[PDB]
Amino acid sequence: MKVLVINAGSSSLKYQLIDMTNESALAVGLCERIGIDNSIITQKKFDGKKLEKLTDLPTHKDALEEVVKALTDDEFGVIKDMGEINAVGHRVVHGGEKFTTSALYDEGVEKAIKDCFELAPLHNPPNMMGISACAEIMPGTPMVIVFDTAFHQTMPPYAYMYALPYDLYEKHGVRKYGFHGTSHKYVAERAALMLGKPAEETKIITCHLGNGSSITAVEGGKSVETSMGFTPLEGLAMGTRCGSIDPAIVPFLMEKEGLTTREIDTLMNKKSGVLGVSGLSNDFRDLDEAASKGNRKAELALEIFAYKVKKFIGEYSAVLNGADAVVFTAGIGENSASIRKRILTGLDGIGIKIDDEKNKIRGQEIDISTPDAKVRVFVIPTNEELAIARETKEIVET
Amino acid sequence: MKVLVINAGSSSLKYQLIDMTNESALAVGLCERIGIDNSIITQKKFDGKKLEKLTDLPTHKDALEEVVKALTDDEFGVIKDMGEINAVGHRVVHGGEKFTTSALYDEGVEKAIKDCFELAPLHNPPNMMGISACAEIMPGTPMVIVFDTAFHQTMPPYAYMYALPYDLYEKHGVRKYGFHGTSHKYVAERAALMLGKPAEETKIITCHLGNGSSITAVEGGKSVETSMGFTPLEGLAMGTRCGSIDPAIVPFLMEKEGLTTREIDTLMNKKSGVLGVSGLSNDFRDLDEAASKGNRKAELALEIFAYKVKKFIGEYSAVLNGADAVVFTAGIGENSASIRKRILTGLDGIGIKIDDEKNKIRGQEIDISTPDAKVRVFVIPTNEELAIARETKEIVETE
Ligand SMILES: Nc1ncnc2c1ncn2[C@@H]1O[C@H](COP(=O)(O)OP(=O)(O)O)[C@@H](O)[C@@H]1O
Ligand SMILES: Nc1ncnc2c1ncn2[C@@H]1O[C@H](COP(=O)(O)OP(=O)(O)O)[C@@H](O)[C@H]1O
């Protein structure tokens, strides 16, 4: 099979054509300035052959037509007919809640995706401009919609429920949903491999550390617990998010600062995290340097961040009654041996130990734990497009 | 010296006259339905004598007057007159960052307590009513105040700091405070003893499960982290407290129902917890009964509670890098073998096992963990009163 993973944008359209027989990215491209002028489409064939074309792209519908022209090119393409694409994937975050499985996008899925709109204080809704374009260009083609919150639908009631009046979950659907589902599920499957055992007999703690970070407890290959909840705000302190602070602080600030419902929300999701603590930046590579340069704020901010992730490794250690391995992925988890150490140091009491040398290695699936460590600690890079591809396949297959 | 410890609530008043000389508790009482119907005071003497008086108690002032009477009863009492009460130790949950240590009562302390009301709406207000009633019945008696936040004052910056705009820390003093200190500290000392090791060489997980629940990670007899934060709402789910939910739920709920900051606050501190889930009550005993009799809401309520305390045990295990013991105390943790069984089940992976039989034992300091368990699990009754008593004596004695 061959899957085309799409990713709609404001005025762009990223794509990948993956051959699922070897999970090889045959081609990779990106459309830009869609609707705007000076439109361009850039493609890169696996065998080192980039192609650029300056054709105006009025609508993503047209842009998608060019993506096909690029794949079909015999000199810079990788497929003769458009009929070689038997599946298309699209990742969805908000509007995805309440979906236990990846839908095969039919007439009843737009509404479903259009329902979780206002529902939950979610910013940028599902950019459908790039999804509806498939129904046109290639109708007789399977289109799967991957949900970043579906992976956590296996969580038990005593976990996704809040100790709040039951009518809230019943009247507004207030429950813990979780995110980074595709990333968490991908590395999970990977970890099980490196453990040399069936995913069914493995207890893994997956750590997605990026601008928005999230931890998940993976038992027998299913999400049983996750750090985020109703919204991505719950959980670890991250780039600009506050995380799980004292709920009472929310209304407190609103009164002491004469704020609005929207002002407090912005401050927790945009003006907080390491950005608000360091007062310097939300980007970690920057905070890391500032820190080593003697910057108190930055340093403090990094201590909070690592500390919270550490606390979570422990919290999920209980939730899973013993953890076989811990996985670190995403931007921070993959390139920062610095923060990985801050996090993993001082956990030998719970079976965690890391080989400072293997830890230095960057970008590579490696087991940075010591050989005597009771718990393995893997560093697995997340391949999103490939994850969306595996999913679309699983659906189209079954 | 004989100290009188007060623990006032919105309609109750737990008192206890302790004789600091030999440190023996003379009498223990409890006033209920203060301000409501069928007000009632109860007292138990050191020899088992129980008194009960059914009289109207409109204000705490009245209740306290009746306490003096109950304490000076001819046969069921312990003192001949109010004068034998040398000092009064009062409990106060929040003192602000302006008062993080026990101190003699004066207009300054009173001001601070009155201002921290918004930081402890369920407690400070009622605690103040006690200090007040106390100033009206025994104006000539010294009063020392002990704060629930003192014990956690040793938490490191990377723990009491929230990941919010730093100026909010300097501007409104927002940081984690923690509560139930007096309790956490006591049972911690006891855990060291049961371990037969010097406090400075221990790592304990103290769990105070009661109307209000909180867990603390004590390292070397020092509070390093606690479940509650700025106010007593953060942390575990409670009788009527939601605990640490998703902050983003506050603005959402507020807009979805045009709730006001005052309202949403009331919903989080009074309508949530196991009360909100079960839709039945905040009493863990009633919930325990209802659950077993087929009540799902109550069933789920206790499930959610036991699960939350479980995770913290796991959380603070990473904080202490291997805990030496997990200590259970307070209303629930002391008496509910039931709830404890829910919490401790399925933790052998992190080295925790319990002897289901020893776990049935009532209120007694007993180690309910298997002899081979890598982690001890003591069931230690709390003694907030002797603690406050000692504090009171110290402050007053030392001028
Ligand atoms: N035998 C018991 N079984 C179950 N829960 C109990 C029991 N005894 C006490 N509790 C729990 O403790 C709560 C009150 O404890 P706490 O807050 O420490 O106050 P108090 O000073 O009255 O003990 C009760 O609402 C809840 O049921
Ligand atoms: N070498 C590094 N040192 C520190 N932080 C890094 C490093 N590499 C990546 N990061 C983190 O990853 C982020 C990358 O953002 P992005 O590519 O969108 O991925 P993510 O979703 O993981 O954040 C950077 O802002 C930084 O926070």
Image: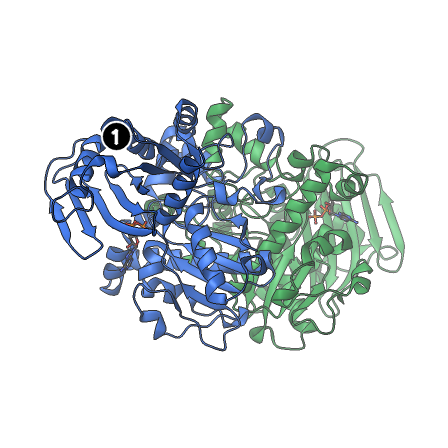
Chain colours: A green, B blue
Q: Amino acid at mark 1?
A: Met
Residue under the image location 42 percent in, 65 percent down: B378
Q: Point out residue B213 in the picture as x, y percentages from the top left corner.
A: 39, 50
Residue closer to the observer: B227 or B139: B139
Residue under the image location 42 percent in, 72 percent down: B354
Q: Quadrant of the C terminus of chain B?
A: top left
Please indicate whether residue A100 sits to the left or right of residue B259 in the image: right
Please indicate whether residue A278 sits to the left or right of residue B138 in the image: right
In the image, residue B174 above or below residue A153: above
Instruction: For mark 1, give the secondary structure.
Output: loop
Residue closer to the observer: B177 or B13: B13
* Residue that sits furthest to the left in the current view: B54
Q: Point out residue A152 in the picture as x, y percentages from the top left corner.
A: 52, 58
Residue A218 seen in the figure: yes
Q: Quadrant of residue A300?
A: top right
Please indicate whether residue A47 sits to the left or right of residue B397 in the image: right
Q: Which residue corresponds to mark 1?
A: B138
Residue under the image location 35 percent in, 35 percent down: B266
Q: Point out residue A349 in the picture as x, y percentages from the top left corner.
A: 62, 65
Q: Quadrant of the N terminus of chain B?
A: top left
Q: Point out residue A171 in the picture as x, y percentages from the top left corner.
A: 35, 44
